[PDB]
Amino acid sequence: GVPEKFATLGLTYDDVLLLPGASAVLPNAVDTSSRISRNVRVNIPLLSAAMDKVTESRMAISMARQGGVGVLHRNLSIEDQANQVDLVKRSESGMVANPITIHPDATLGEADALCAKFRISGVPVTDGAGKLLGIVTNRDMAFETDRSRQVREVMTPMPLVTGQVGISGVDAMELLRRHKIEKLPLVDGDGILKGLITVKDFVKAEQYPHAAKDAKGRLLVGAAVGASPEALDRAQALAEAGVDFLVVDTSHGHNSNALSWMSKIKSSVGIDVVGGNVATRDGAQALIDAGVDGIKVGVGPGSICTTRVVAGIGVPQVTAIYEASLAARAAGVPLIGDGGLQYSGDIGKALAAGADTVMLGSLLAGCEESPGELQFINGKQFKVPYRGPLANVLHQLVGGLRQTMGYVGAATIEEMESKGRFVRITSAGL
Amino acid sequence: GVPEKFATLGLTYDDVLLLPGASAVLPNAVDTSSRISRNVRVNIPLLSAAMDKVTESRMAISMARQGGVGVLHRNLSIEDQANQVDLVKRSESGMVANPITIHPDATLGEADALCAKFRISGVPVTDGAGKLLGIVTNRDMAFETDRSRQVREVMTPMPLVTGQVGISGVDAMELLRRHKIEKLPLVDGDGILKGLITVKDFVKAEQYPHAAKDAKGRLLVGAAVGASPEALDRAQALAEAGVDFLVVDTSHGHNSNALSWMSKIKSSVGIDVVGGNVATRDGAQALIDAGVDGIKVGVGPGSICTTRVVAGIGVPQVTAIYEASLAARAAGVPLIGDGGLQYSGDIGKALAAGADTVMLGSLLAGCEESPGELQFINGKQFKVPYRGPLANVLHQLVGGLRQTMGYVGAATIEEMESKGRFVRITSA
Amino acid sequence: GVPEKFATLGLTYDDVLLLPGASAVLPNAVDTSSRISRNVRVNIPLLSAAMDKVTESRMAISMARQGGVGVLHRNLSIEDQANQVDLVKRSESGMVANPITIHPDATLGEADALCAKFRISGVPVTDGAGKLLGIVTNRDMAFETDRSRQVREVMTPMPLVTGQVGISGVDAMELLRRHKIEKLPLVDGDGILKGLITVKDFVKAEQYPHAAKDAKGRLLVGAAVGASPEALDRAQALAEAGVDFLVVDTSHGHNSNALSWMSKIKSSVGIDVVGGNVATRDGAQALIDAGVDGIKVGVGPGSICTTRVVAGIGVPQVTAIYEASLAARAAGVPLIGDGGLQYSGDIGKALAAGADTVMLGSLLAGCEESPGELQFINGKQFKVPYRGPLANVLHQLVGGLRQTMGYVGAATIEEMESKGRFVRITSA
Amino acid sequence: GVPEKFATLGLTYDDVLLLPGASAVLPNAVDTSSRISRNVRVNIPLLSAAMDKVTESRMAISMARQGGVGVLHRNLSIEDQANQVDLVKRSESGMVANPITIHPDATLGEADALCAKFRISGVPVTDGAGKLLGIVTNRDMAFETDRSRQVREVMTPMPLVTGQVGISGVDAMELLRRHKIEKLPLVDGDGILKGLITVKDFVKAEQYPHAAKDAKGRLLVGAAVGASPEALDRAQALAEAGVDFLVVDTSHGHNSNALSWMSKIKSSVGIDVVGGNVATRDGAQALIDAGVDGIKVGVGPGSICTTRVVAGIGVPQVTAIYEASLAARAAGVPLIGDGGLQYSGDIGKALAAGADTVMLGSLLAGCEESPGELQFINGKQFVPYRGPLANVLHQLVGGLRQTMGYVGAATIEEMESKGRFVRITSA
Ligand SMILES: Nc1nc2c(ncn2[C@@H]2O[C@H](COP(=O)(O)OP(=O)(O)O)[C@@H](OP(=O)(O)OP(=O)(O)O)[C@H]2O)c(=O)[nH]1
Ligand SMILES: Nc1nc2c(ncn2[C@@H]2O[C@H](COP(=O)(O)OP(=O)(O)O)[C@@H](OP(=O)(O)OP(=O)(O)O)[C@H]2O)c(=O)[nH]1
Ligand SMILES: Nc1nc2c(ncn2[C@@H]2O[C@H](COP(=O)(O)OP(=O)(O)O)[C@@H](OP(=O)(O)OP(=O)(O)O)[C@H]2O)c(=O)[nH]1
Ligand SMILES: Nc1nc2c(ncn2[C@@H]2O[C@H](COP(=O)(O)OP(=O)(O)O)[C@@H](OP(=O)(O)OP(=O)(O)O)[C@H]2O)c(=O)[nH]1
Ligand SMILES: Nc1ncnc2c1ncn2[C@@H]1O[C@H](COP(=O)(O)OP(=O)(O)OP(=O)(O)O)[C@@H](O)[C@H]1O
Ligand SMILES: Nc1ncnc2c1ncn2[C@@H]1O[C@H](COP(=O)(O)OP(=O)(O)OP(=O)(O)O)[C@@H](O)[C@H]1O
Ligand SMILES: Nc1ncnc2c1ncn2[C@@H]1O[C@H](COP(=O)(O)OP(=O)(O)OP(=O)(O)O)[C@@H](O)[C@H]1O
Ligand SMILES: Nc1ncnc2c1ncn2[C@@H]1O[C@H](COP(=O)(O)OP(=O)(O)OP(=O)(O)O)[C@@H](O)[C@H]1O
Ligand SMILES: [Mg+2]
Ligand SMILES: [Mg+2]
Ligand SMILES: [Mg+2]
Ligand SMILES: [Mg+2]
Ligand SMILES: [Mg+2]
Ligand SMILES: [Mg+2]
Ligand SMILES: [Mg+2]
């Protein structure tokens, strides 16, 4: 009973429910892996948002360890954001081919700061030519009080227990078990340091068996850039640091200038580039025509959010995802749902509506791994209420998603769009 | 104005109303009987849910006395659940062919514990062959202080006033009246005890004239089982104890393994087997194809309930009942509405939408007959706010249904689906 | 304008404030040490209460490390409470003269369980005569997958780096630094194991420089007992495990039977015994006459708490402390304030009113170190809202007390009673 | 019915009321002048607190124009605080002997920045020796777009209408009127600039006839310093910039080290030094013995405030003022009531209890003249926006005049004797 100008009805997550369907698969047996972009895969379909209150290196590391991925925020210098990337890539199994080093004339303070930075308990000591001279570890410094003392005075000097480039995990773990050590430098025939294996690599692989990793076995990570000449310089620095994909993050992804920078940034790097944000079919198509490898969907998804109140602009998120998916699914381009979430059950709704993954934002701002210092004022806060470890949040969200997939009969994420049947509900049902 | 992926609108009870229609029948004259399953009938269209806070024997007994039926929960051992079944079946008129007995060397404590267990005021005393030796009753023990004293010392010994196998109610009552006694053992020609009638059988028949009973005149009762190998052992034990139907209770009735166990639980017993839960036409058809004698409908029926919040899964209950009824009515399989209730008027809505009965849940957890212990903390609670006797809840619910039926013109539940006309309403 | 029967006005913490006074001492320079009892001293004047939701070994260890002390609750078996004591006493520097050991035939699973129990990363391996055979540590077991494997197969055998009984801290650390090891077994001339030093002893001494310790350098701990024959057996078992003081915990410390058991318990052990609870001068004097080494003050201290509502019994806590201190100060017996706290500033008020230390209760139940299990239900809770590490609670409380002492001019706790001047305030 | 240790009852403003008394004086006729310290006088008995959200130069100027005084906060460098002092002292009539100047080689941007800084509409242009070359004013720059143009190109050059040092207000005004100009440079016989009069001096004197001023006719101002070697240097820098009194501002005024610095600072300057904070008779006496010229009273005056909750320390403010005044009134040392205010009626209560003036704090943080930036977020904010200070002070002073009329006090000094108190219950 409305004119055509107003015919379309937009739906939010609360407006719809998924129906139970014929199922031969239990929640604990479904596969939750999905694609961030054409060439980036995760083991749970969740990202942490590129917000300065949410994702720096510690959050990105935990997300990837749990099988998702973090998108490092860009509200910091190029050098600081690239450093955040490096910390993620060189977290565990990341020093097999790019180890940290220290010169023997350095102080213990410099060595300990490096150990704290990369969260590891030792540094190979090398000369200017990269020849291995020895190794200084936490135990060598445990009883040292003078931080000005030189590394050479406390390090364990060569000859050390070492391995060859390409040593297998089983063989490297047999040199840490036989010699009662936790570190294994990798050297070439001339004794030049080529890599480093430590017990951390094996401990973290066992504790986090579903970690999302790159082809080199290092934790996956993404990073946000803007749409500007500066964003191009930032993109290059992040690619050099080893980032696995870029997110060109704009409030209006359908702006022609933003689209142009997406194309320019994409053509200037060899890694996947995600573009956003859009909330319509034609906007998603414009991003695809601009060449992005994934799209991010969400413009004014939240009730009485800023763009809605200030500008009257917005799209209910189920409709936004569905409309964008008409273009994205037709092109085979993964779709990230970004905004409007209110329950773990909304994840399955997003996937059945056409999303491949879902980005989590303010929900992860109170988590231990988010940036900011934990402060105490009668209760615990992040300087936002303290929520505890990320792992507890993700376990509940992924547990919920597995329930949805079992109820719908989807053994894989790719089956969700076809097997998920929707019903709309009224405000009485809500 | 939505894409077809989202065309369907689901309706809950609050979304609709029933219209008044042409009527020639008053509320006090309508018939409220309905079917639980193909071969199980009740006198009011209501069940108590298989929740451990709701239905054990006391709840099941009261439900059946009021004309409904209870579904005994399964959060207990097979032997404990079978015992709950036995307590219901042998409540009133249930010992005519399976009496309790005690040996003459038993203590008064053992006899009184048996009386308390079955809520009967005496025990026939027999020897190892079943020969009736006497009877010990509440009055025989009233003034006794030593609980170790042997039954034989206080029992009334044979010869007793007894009845024959097959004695009628009228004849049994006349014997009780004439001899001013409350118990009538039933014996065969050799004096072997075959059954027992007590005044409770007549008192409860008069107090509860609409009791739901089996073909032998014993209170009806159901019991829940899971979907697993253990559920098959449980089913056999419950059937042996005299349960009238089984409810294969699963959260996702459309799961292939759950459906398979339904066909394995149904084919292994001779009593009716209900399956659930489903909320779609295709789900109901899958239950029917698996061979169940009734279906239970309800998946995420409640606003912001657990499956909805955790998993985003759910179906508004009016739509769920209607869609499932499209399959159930064509197959002649009764449909139990399980969940989403908020008012007594919702019962009539469920029936007009296609349900045959409605299962009551947390509503009843506060009733006197629920398993919890009544405790006092400034006010009364169950250890859940105390609601009082089940009878008060059912009286209001059944009274409401009779009003609906009078307004719609339905003289029977079976007329509700055709005569009940709906209108949707807005939030205003 | 009231009868003499009602002349006395009782004051709670909120009724009074402390005045600023002449001061030559800054908050960061005051001394916060005080006495729990005649012969037990702490570095901050705070105890954790003997409640089963608050203080087991983990809470007691953290309290002592921060300079206070925990009182282990008694809602568990005698052997379990004594085990809790043992865990505290042998936390750090507690195995120098009483080490844990394991047979060479024991499994890695058994060795790891012992390491987890005492929060130590290795076990000396000995024979039945206590002769040292080797040592098995976390690194020896790090890559092992079979938990049934023998410890002798993965352990480092003698000869080990060892020290003499009585080795100094500097000398032991020198051995750990030169041999790049974390353990130093202590042996006699015949190679019998006499003690164990590990890097934990040095790490924890550096991290917690204000730890409250006994004469042997082990963390202080108290434990609660009741007032009954069983409490006498419990007291002995706790004393044997190395507890530093006992708290006879009753709600009516002025009961003649409770007073009698305090004397009996006091006379049956050699360690300090605290008695409570009381809230009057005559009650404190009765505890003192019974022979206790400290008193605990608090009977119905909180507005609309249970004893007040149920029984109308209670004493505002400032009055309770002051009245009890009239007896306790004359006898030189320390006074523990137990209850009624609402602000960190109430600590200074209690001390100025006559308390020597203050017991903290439900405040701490939400701390990480409390016995409950940390669970996540949208937010973090203990099974009570999760508050985080004890250290921040104590840091805020001790910081506030230091502010109080600076304002009043008290350089030491005992100066609080004389230099702390009070003013009463109205509800405005 | 309590032990002697707890005998004393402390009273706050809400605990008491003043009685009406015999009165022959109406509210509009009472005199509201009082003393900040032995040698500093105000026309309304109110100060603005030395909080960085309350009093910088703009707040201090408005307070002084209304007859009170501001105490400039010290959460800034010595040179930044001294600059704040200079801005107040050289607000109106403050350049008669210390004018701003600019060189002919300066730009219009630099000239306009100076005019904006001192809120003056022109700058005398001088050479390096101070010889007057001309004057550049707002009207000279009104139509100038280039902000890099040199002042010499747009200034009015000498010969200007000038006056001599010591010219009277009446004579200076006649020159401004006769020549239809707003500026009057003051020069010596050699044409060296010695001072400056502008129309602002007369406009502001007429708009603010009760402006609290010093002996030279410049707006009064105070400034806070700490209790430390750095505060001794800060005190000298503030006294060189022309501050009229210092406030040695500590959370614990009865601390021996704080008292020692009060004595050291007092003896190192020639201006009045106020010390605080205290809340007892012995604390006030210790401040007096240290040599201060006024005391500030208030330690944990507010219900469930920080010092009360964290440390259990505090004194209800009526008791604090009364007890401190027992020492203050005996020595003739003025007493500043600092904290606990909740109504305009509490001012009269403070004065009747023994205070000479009352310091206003967070109340004023929302006023236009407070340091914060006025921002619009659906509504106006700085805390909520309160508008001009004048509106707050008008209501507060109006209330005090009502109190004095009801009590019969023609002067502030009569409040202590004529103000009769009654305590009230929570009912
Ligand atoms: N010097 C120094 N070392 C740090 C610091 N933080 C962590 N480490 C060390 O790096 C390794 C990894 O620490 P984790 O805390 O578990 O790493 P994670 O953040 O990536 O999860 C550990 O050594 P490990 O040898 O791999 O394991 P383990 O021997 O401690 O068991 C740890 O001792 C620090 O701030 N300074
Ligand atoms: N020894 C013993 N008897 C119990 C106990 N509980 C109930 N009874 C008796 O069993 C019969 C049923 O009691 P009800 O209370 O009416 O049974 P109900 O729970 O099934 O409704 C009564 O005897 P009746 O002869 O059938 O009726 P009446 O003579 O009491 O009127 C009653 O006295 C018990 O705990 N111990
Ligand atoms: N096998 C085993 N060891 C445990 C366990 N819990 C703690 N530990 C070990 O005991 C020592 C104390 O751990 P903490 O966590 O600091 O002790 P705490 O509870 O008393 O504070 C550490 O070894 P350390 O050598 O003293 O310190 P470090 O080598 O880790 O630096 C730690 O590795 C456990 O559950 N199982
Ligand atoms: N160039 C410039 N001038 C400013 C600025 N702010 C104030 N003025 C001028 O200085 C004099 C004081 O302005 P006020 O607003 O009254 O000063 P106030 O802050 O102390 O109250 C006025 O000139 P007047 O000649 O004394 O008065 P009138 O001719 O404006 O009436 C005014 O035009 C500024 O930011 N830049
Ligand atoms: N590959 C190696 N060859 C020789 N010595 C080594 C080697 N790796 C480590 N060390 C030395 O062995 C000793 C133990 O160091 P390791 O790396 O095994 O543990 P750590 O991380 O310092 O110990 P902890 O886990 O107790 O903090 C140190 O002196 C270290 O320098
Ligand atoms: N069939 C019977 N023949 C003979 N005596 C009987 C018979 N049934 C019961 N009695 C005896 O009659 C007396 C009354 O018992 P009855 O069963 O009538 O009532 P009750 O339930 O014990 O009493 P109450 O209802 O007062 O609690 C008892 O001594 C009982 O032993
Ligand atoms: N006193 C000792 N003499 C000889 N070997 C020792 C001695 N103490 C420990 N070891 C051996 O040294 C190796 C290192 O053990 P240590 O006690 O130093 O700690 P760890 O178990 O390696 O701890 P971490 O978890 O910190 O790596 C182990 O093989 C242990 O058996
Ligand atoms: N003492 C003076 N002698 C000569 N000319 C002067 C003198 N003072 C100002 N002028 C010049 O007179 C003109 C008017 O300036 P004046 O100071 O009177 O007002 P203004 O503050 O610049 O203007 P307005 O009040 O309109 O903003 C300007 O050219 C100014 O240079
Ligand atoms: Mg290590
Ligand atoms: Mg270690
Ligand atoms: Mg009877
Ligand atoms: Mg160790
Ligand atoms: Mg280690
Ligand atoms: Mg002008
Ligand atoms: Mg003008």
Image (tube, coloured by chain):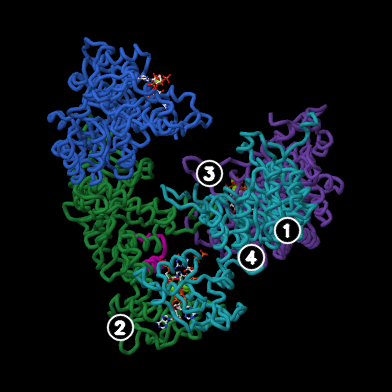
Chain colours: A green, B blue, C cyan, D purple
Circles 1, 2 touching at the beta carbon (< 8 Å): no
Q: For the residues marked 1 and 3, what is the alpha-carbon distance in whole angstroms?
A: 59 Å
According to the image, label 2 marks what residue? Answer: A164
Image location (x, y in percent) of residue D151: 55, 60
* Magenta stretch, residue numbers: A70-85
Q: Residue at 44% across / 65% down in the picture?
A: C113
Tag 4 residue: C213
Q: Which residue is mark 3?
A: D381
Q: Nearer the viewer, mark 4 or mark 3?
A: 4
Q: Quadrant of the C terminus of chain B?
A: top left
Left or right: B251, with C396 as reference point: left
Q: Say if labels 3 and 2 share a chain.
A: no
Q: Nearer the viewer, mark 1 or mark 2?
A: 1
Q: Which residue is mark 1?
A: C38
Q: Nearer the viewer, residue B115 or D135?
A: B115
| Dot in front, 3 or 2 | 2
Q: Quadrant of residue D68?
A: top right
Discs 1 and 3 share one subunit = no
* Mark 2 closeness class: few <14, some 14–19, many ≥20 residues within 10 Å: some
Q: CA distance from mark 3 to mark 2?
A: 67 Å
Q: Secondary structure at mark 3?
A: strand
Q: Amino acid at mark 2?
A: Gln
